[PDB]
């Protein structure tokens, strides 16, 4: 029965560390929102793109900071014990950088760069790292955004934007079958990529079928 | 044993006030129907819009009255004890005003104005107020209506109506991520907003891709 | 869009008050546990009853205090806006008093006395009151406890305990039909009272069918 | 190429999984054996010590396969693959807690469980026994010991129930002495009162017919 | 589209008659409660039986009246169109009479007598009748009550009460297999009769196993 | 105990009449299927419509017959005692006529005509009648069919079919709000009418949104 | 681009889809017969006297099923057993349970697989012809648990206080032979696992009897 | 009780053969992926077609081998007892050849040729054969691919590709009504063919309405 008092001394600690961690993550959900809202502008005002990439980078330079405090909360080797506390809001952010990197310089941001921009490592040995599964589920979110971008881009006159997209999403669908995912929780999300490529193909059809 | 007779004296009262309250609410459901049916006309006859906004305002000027009687039934400080009796049929009506405000003057009706048109306060201190969570869930119903409007509007020739919508729904999706809802009963209903914006984007595509 | 910034200024407040309120309630769940665990002793050691009623009262004298702080967190007229935060852990506690009142003095604690022991009122006009629906759902929990008590009491030799119970639960089933509940969330919990009375009848059978007395 | 590097790592996590299910499958197999043999106690009270024995021959084996499981899991990745065995460990923690009760009439310590399976008691020291898993294990003792109390009276032993309702009695005690917050385990503690229910009922049935051996 | 206005003129009438009918039935639910609460006394005070049969008969004499008003609401030949509005609260009452008839005179109340005490007919030709399926489902409720009675009766000293019950419930289980119900909504309720006879047998066991019938 | 023997003499009768009635209804489910399967053709071969309306009418002329035998099984004034035995497979058939009436002559079949084609009355006084609630729940089934018809019609080239539909389903949605159903078992089925009108609107969109090009 | 290739296709595709409706037709007659036996055997839960009477009717049912079964064999082309197997793997479990019940009611032991085929006019190997799928046989006499737990319960209702004890040795040896297995997790592994909950109340019922129960001067 | 030990001796064998069969099939799912991914290139680079048909044929020449091993695992006359283990991943492959046969030589691959390229027979008498129902459900997968091809083809300039497709898919829709499928599991999949022909017609419209050909 003292056995159960020792239990409370440990159980208070794990449950205190959780509310402390949700607290940091809540600040990161808050920062993420800001970037995503601002980047929404790109579906109606193509001129504000670079303007908006900018704000979003002001957001990311901040996120890194709160992330580093998240590391001071997690005890070493316990990464995956509390992982589910941020695996989401990191995908939410990996998608945000991958978009901004495509908008700016028209290629696909490396995993390594993402960690560079958020103050992580690229192996859990070196410290608080970027879960490689999280990274992927992030830049998979690029499909749903870039199919809406292709549609909204033709709305605003830019008739080249679709073709350039279907080569990016084209090489992106390429690298996901070049995989060989086995049926897990992520296999499901890759399978819904074909429907995004679907309307991106359709949109490239619509342009060069009217010579627009 | 008398303890249980006193119980009946109070238990008759709460259950009498309930049937009295359903009675008022039923009259308000009835009035709401009328407005919603008449505003349905906008999906087939663009000329009857102002005509239909009109009938609906005749409906609202009435609802306020029944609403004030609902206040004479509810004992002070018991607002949320019977709240569930009308939280629905108020969202049903908040949507009706927000639609009529958009149709007429092309902007988004304030929460304060909604109470002004129904004879409520804007704080439960001042009296029978408009639950701020109810207001929100009301003007979220605007998405499902205005996506159908955008579709039915092009059916009837008006090719500008979509573009104007996707800026309204555009600034509306903006203010909902500018939030940071935590996963409750309303978080679910905001998430199904992206699918409405989906076909509103698609429709703005359809117009300026054939130029009409 | 400023409209949505004002929104955050209010929305932070309602959601701050919630975590502040769960915090108080959590302290009350903690105190409640203590009382309920200690009163579990009555199912194996009939000698520790008064001893255990005592500990539980030390628990209640404390609960009242945290309850009064809960009142300083709730803004007037908003009782039922956050009611669901404690309607449970009050039934949990109304049952605890009704049990301790039955164990000690063999009758049924008044609603008014329950509020007197927790520093509440008996009307939401006067202030932070004891929700009369909560009170009932509490002393309905007495059935499941006192059926187990009647069973465990015969285990330990006391052959009068069942008969005395079936007159308490007897007059208690009486007052609940003397009602006329209409089918809500509480109508369901009254209906599962007949199954408690069931084994309490059965236990009174078992004793005076073997002329068992002590 | 970014997506080819991806395959080189993605093959590894998915190879380690099938390698880990493989070890676990061997541990499910061993577990069954012990549980089946301990089923005997519901019909032949004489085979108890006999059956505790076979079960211990099973446990001495499980530890071994467990230590190989540790050579498969990379350090600090404990909880990345935890869900692969959190079940089949509760399955086994229940198996020892039963055998410890059958033999020596008290409740096996968490520390001893690890001692019998070659684990640590902290994830710092290495592959440890997840303290949440341990609990969910010795909660499985209620469903077994209520059936034991019932089947025990069937076979004549009229003291067995009373001794159970003090074990399950002190066990229900330590679970309210907790203060679980509503998670996945809170749900399983709540269904403990229905097990104590029929264990009380059975202690009633014996000493209400004055039954004593 | 006038076609749909005519529709409203009829649809208001059926839905008005329903609220009018629930209104009568609600009064009958109210009266039924009274009887059933008062007859509950027999489980703790064997002396108040005849006293309680009495109050219950005061309730039935009343129910008949409201019933006859229910007949003035139901248009002829529409009996089964609104049947589901009272098939319950009639079983609730058929059980109440069958109990009072058993308590008083120790036999089983005829279907014909039940209608006589409620002002109905015994064929839907003659008018508002007592649905024979409803009657049965009523005096099937006798099992759950008289098994609790047998149990509570021994509690209070009356050691003959069980034996007398197991011959009533005995002849009752007899007439239900003498049937040949085909699997419907009522077949299910007859099957749960065996569990009532179960403890009624058990209770007759418990008495004459400690020698409590005078002999 | 004889009281319970008399009971069996009656209880055999109600339960015999039930199997006799399910027997008639089973023959009517069978005939119904035939009509509905043949009318499915309209979703792929617009030329077989009149051909298929025909087969379906050969089915209905038959159903009436079995229906009249169902009347000889039901004792007068017991209509609603066994109603639940066919309230379904009549909605199944009321939808079948309403579809064939729309396909042929482009308007909405009267309740009175439905009874005329099945040998019923229009009041339970006159005899075995067509339950007016059943009639409604039938021609509500028209929505799910005619939305799929509008979609499959554009597939096959007929670009006028949708517009004509959205005026039929348009006036049909009109008469259902012109109601004032109170929340029962049928209120639920009317509410799921808006989702059928939804895609029918969408389809009319898709047609008249595909006009011309530049001309240079 | 040839198009006759797709006409030949119709000539074969009409045949497999005709044989299916022909096969459902036979199976429908067998579902019909099965019902009869199961309904009549339901009587045992309320009238212990009608057992032998009811075993009888059910055997009149099985003597008939065999016949329709042999016609089902004339519809299935050799070596295509498992191509249409899913058309009857259910309604055979339905019947394997019916025999295993009647064999237990009658002579108190467990019917052999070989005997089941003997009573239905099958073989015991798909070489010899239309056989009794061994997986089907098992899934049948697993249905015995749900029936015999309800029987033990309904038996004590009607006075027979030995019936439970006799059941818990049959179900006892039956639970024995199922762990003596080593099923790997498939579609049948799931159905064996729900056997412990049937043994549960059968143990409970043997408890209830020999716990009642008295020790007087 | 020994009756149930003999049972285990057979039951281990059927469940060992299953894991052995899933093992071969898994290797064939792996090879199939390779062909399908590589043939995806045709939707963006019309020059790599013949290049990609080639890689895919290097994949098929391999598949046949693993297939022949699958035959050494299946006991004769038990074809359909384990059929459900590969009926999918063969449609997956029948589609892969039918596509590569269309891309190369512009006609429709015979069922007989499919077996020739995979080392099967064309009757279950002769041995491990190609289930004719599987073959069909394969070359039905041609519609979804060739509608996307017609769309992506005009994207890349080739304005004749649609017209040629609508005669292939045209003669293919022809042979499927020339059928008379009865409502089973495959009747459903043929019915969703009209929606593929739909956009294929639409695309032929789009080209010769801006006279991109003729």
Image (spheres, coloured by chain):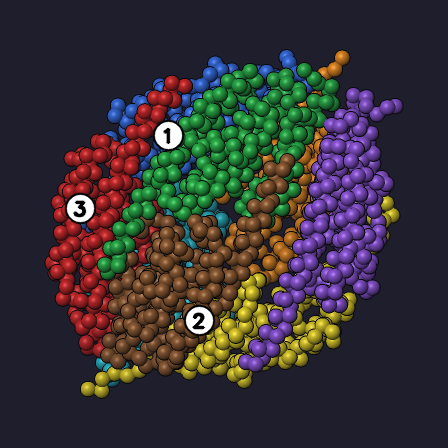
Chain colours: A red, B brown, C green, D blue, E purple, F yellow, G orange, H cyan
Secondary structure of residue under mark 2: helix
From the viewer's perspective, tell me whether residue G209 is left or right of residue A74. right
Q: In the rendering, at what x and y percent does residue A69 appear?
A: 18, 38
Please give the residue where the numbered disc 3 appears in the rendered image.
A63
Q: In the rendering, at what x and y percent does residue C133 appear?
A: 52, 42
From the viewer's perspective, tell me whether residue A116 is left or right of residue C120. left
The reply to whether label 2 and label 3 mark residues of one chain is: no
Please give the residue where the numbered disc 1 appears in the rendered image.
D132
Residue at horizontal 28 percent and vertical 62 percent from the top: B172
The reply to whether label 2 and label 1 mark residues of one chain is: no
Q: Is residue E193 visible?
A: no
From this view, report whether residue B150 is shown above or below residue H120: below
| Of marks 2 and 3, the one in the foreground | 2
What chain is tagged by disc 2?
B
CA gap, disc 2 and disc 1:
60 Å
CA gap, disc 2 and disc 3:
50 Å
């Amino acid at each position: 029965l003292d056995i159960f008092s020792n239990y409370q001394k440990y159980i208070d600690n794990e449950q205190e560390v959780r509310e402390n961690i949700r607290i940091v993550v809540r600040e990161i959900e808050h920062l993420s929102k800001e970037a995503q809202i601002k980047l929404q502008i790109i579906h109606s005002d193509l001129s504000q793109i670079s303007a908006a990439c900018g704000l979003a980078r002001k957001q990311v330079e901040l996120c890194a900071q709160k992330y580093q405090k998240l590391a001071e909360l997690v005890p070493a080797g316990q990464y995956y014990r509390y992982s589910d506390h941020w695996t989401f809001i990191t995908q939410r952010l990996i998608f945000i950088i991958a978009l901004v990197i495509y908008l700016e310089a028209g290629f696909l941001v490396t995993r390594e760069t993402v960690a560079e921009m958020l103050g992580l490592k690229i192996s859990q040995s070196e410290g608080f790292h970027l879960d490689v599964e999280d990274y992927l589920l992030g830049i998979l979110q690029l499909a749903s955004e870039l199919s809406r971008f292709a549609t909204n881009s033709v709305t605003m006159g830019d008739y080249e934007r679709p073709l350039n997209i279907s080569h990016f999403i084209g090489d992106l669908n390429t690298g996901f079958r070049l995989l060989n995912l086995k049926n897990d929780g992520l296999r499901k999300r890759f399978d819904a990529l074909k429907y995004d490529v679907k309307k991106i193909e359709e949109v490239v059809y619509d342009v060069s079928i009217r010579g627009l």
